[PDB]
Amino acid sequence: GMAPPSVFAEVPQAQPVVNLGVGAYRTDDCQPWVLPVVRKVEQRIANNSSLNHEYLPILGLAEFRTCASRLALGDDSPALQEKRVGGVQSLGGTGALRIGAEFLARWYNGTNNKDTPVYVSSPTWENLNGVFTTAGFKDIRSYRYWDTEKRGLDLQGFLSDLENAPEFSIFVLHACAHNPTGTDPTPEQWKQIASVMKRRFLFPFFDSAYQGFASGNLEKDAWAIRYFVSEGFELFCAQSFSKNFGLYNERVGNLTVVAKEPDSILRVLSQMQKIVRVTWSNPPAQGARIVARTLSDPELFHEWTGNVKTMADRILSMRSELRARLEALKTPGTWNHITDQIGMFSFTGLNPKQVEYLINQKHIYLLPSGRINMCGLTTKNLDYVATSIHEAVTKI
Amino acid sequence: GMAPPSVFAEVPQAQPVLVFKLIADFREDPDPRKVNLGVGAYRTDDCQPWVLPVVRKVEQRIANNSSLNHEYLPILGLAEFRTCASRLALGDDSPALQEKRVGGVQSLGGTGALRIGAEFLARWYNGTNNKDTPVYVSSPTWENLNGVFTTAGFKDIRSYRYWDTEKRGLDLQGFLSDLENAPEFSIFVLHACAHNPTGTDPTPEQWKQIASVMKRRFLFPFFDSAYQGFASGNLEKDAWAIRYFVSEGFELFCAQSFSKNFGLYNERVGNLTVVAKEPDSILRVLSQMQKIVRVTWSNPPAQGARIVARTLSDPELFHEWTGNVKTMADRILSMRSELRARLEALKTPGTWNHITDQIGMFSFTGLNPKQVEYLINQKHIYLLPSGRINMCGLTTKNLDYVATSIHEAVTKIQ
């Protein structure tokens, strides 16, 4: 020993974590797309020399928080009229989930109760377990969701897992465009889910990362959140603007809180502020400024809804086209899930074996789960993808 | 029959934060002589925020570049920003940069850099998941520091002596004693320059004495660098202590903020610089940093980091920026000199050399709580109960009134 040992000497190397594996919108030319409305608002911001760079409030830009919560809940939401809604600007949807998880691990179902079960879908967003584990929750559980045989929602399994969940358990619910399956409950199925959650005092923590982006219509995509509000639930909703505004790298999110009465919102937000202060202090301005300007100008809002529907329509086109080509190519199995599914992501129903074939024989890159991003499909590669799927299904 | 109570019914209302209400009371005050010495950011002689000219210039260049997209940055952040930020702290000629034993994690301001570093240490430093390693912070220190380290899981936060109330400066002997008694491997959070809130910094010779104890007792330096260049106008002088520790062979963290020296407060631009003994550990440390970031903010925002990267990587913009930084530093130096001169011209009891010996925008004036109450209630001069003032709250127009009011407080109160 010649030298003093490094304090990092034992740090482990963390485990490593046509392209159908993208996780962001792409055009038919395989390119990123800055939304036209975003470019317009960025120019207005750049031309406004009165804007300064002083710290935003801990909880964020007030106009953004109000507009974001209105987007999720609806302008005429009774919860908004009754002043029992709070909004915390966050670092994307991830930051909203994290702040909400930190709050619940400190103040929900007792004080510092790390034992409340947290239920996530099987499968779910890959980062969700880490967010809740880091907040201190010791008991993360799964609810049945994807049915591999029917290629759709295992409603009876989901319902049984709700019925068997301890009272006050937290359920993380994808509000629409479930990631990674693309399979959402219908409104009637949502009503059954809500009924069990109401009876068993289960806490809805909605993750709304694809509102409007999902189906092309922002109002339809928020229906489940608004239904839970109308049924009298208190809930959280972690909103991301990464996908529906294409503002991935500006880290724009909002945590909406719905409580029974206004005083509870004040106390909850006061604890939120403490959590934020020691995490990022206060949030960045640029992306929230873009969203606030867009949502508070009816002309910009209308332009934005058009841009969102353009993205959804290109995806809906790729879904309709892929299913038609697979059905035209005498492909075994049912493929109505390709168009029943909603959003960018689709569980194709292909086992890893069929997946390895597409990566090493045909050089389509997709995840072992069979998840594809429909934004990786184009008018130019569709017939090649569809044919290669037909070979993966009939040969391997 | 009765509606059930909210699941939030037992959530307490958090304690009010004093500085927030102080600013609120200042805004309410109708007196035209009122002065806000409680502001937490740079202000011009006309009491205004200042967007740096170089920042406006780079923002226009970014806005006019339609080829930039909004796709996610890497988890660890924009590569050019991380490299430029670490080079600013360590110097172009750093031995650690030459030896490829430096990593940089883009963070949400200095706060985010402190938080990620604390989370890493609580998981991988001095054992696996060792929440018991003592973390030492200065008395007093940055108001949010304890909360950052507590939330990261550290159970034993301690103070080292630092501000000497009687001498209006550094309690070097107390600090050295607290270093000498610190358990081996304890973490010390050290302000690199422009101590917040006191303005009192160790001299280079005092830093050498501090480093000597830390080297001998294997104490870990976690530098907080929020005022590089802003503090004195000289980027190298303001980084001297960090660079001295690197030269002396320390491994260290350095949490860098660009909120003050770029005026980019609301774009949340920071960087955590890691200096390791051997190049191979940087990849391992950064792989764990990635996991921590992923579950906190996923990946960092682009706008502020783009501005900083463009400025630091272009010689013309860099030179303009160093001039903008000097403008801020020089205004603060002027207010310190002018306030001290007036207090001495009024023959105010006590010594006032701390007003110019201190560095950066914050100053522990030495006023006691009752004197602070007098300044707020009788003179409409707003400052913290600790006696902390922001020198940027002083202006050519208010200097006489502030100095006269301080003289009244010192001679009439307590």
Image: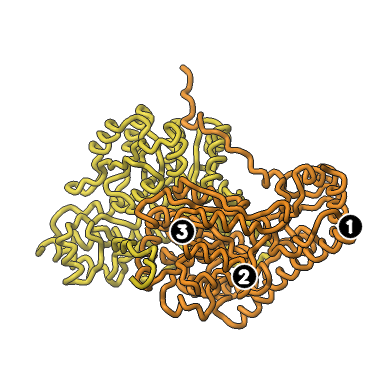
Chain colours: A yellow, B orange
Specify whether B203 is left or right of A189.
right
Q: Amino acid at mark 1?
A: Lys
Q: CA distance from mark 3 to mark 2?
A: 26 Å
Specify whether A139 is left or right of B395.
left
The structure residue drawn at horizontal position 64% and vertical position 43%, both measured from the top left corner, is B17
To which quarter of the image does residue B201 belong?
A: bottom right
Q: Secondary structure at mark 2?
A: helix
Q: CA distance from mark 2 to mark 1?
A: 32 Å
Specify whether A249 is left or right of A288.
left
Instruction: Identify which residue, A375 or A172, lies in the foreground.
Output: A172
Q: Position of residue A7 (x, y in %)?
A: 39, 63
Q: Are marks 1 and 3 on the same chain?
A: yes
The structure residue drawn at horizontal position 28% and vertical position 31%, both measured from the top left corner, is A163
Residue B217 visible in this rendered orientation of the protein: yes
Q: Residues within 10 Å of mark 1 (few under 14, many from 20)?
A: few
Q: Residue furthest right?
A: B346
Judge depth for marks 1 and 3 and give the one in front: 1
The chain ID associated with circle 2 is B
The structure residue drawn at horizontal position 42% and vertical position 69%, both measured from the top left corner, is B276
Q: Are marks 3 and 2 on the same chain?
A: yes
The residue indicated by pointer 2 is B204
For marks 2 and 1 on the same chain, the one whose residue lies earlier in the sequence: 2
Q: Amino acid at mark 2?
A: Pro
The residue indicated by pointer 1 is B347
The residue indicated by pointer 3 is B117
Q: Amino acid at mark 3?
A: Gly
Residue A44 visible in this rendered orientation of the protein: no
Q: Position of residue A89 (x, y in %)?
A: 53, 50
Q: Position of residue B210 (x, y in %)?
A: 56, 63
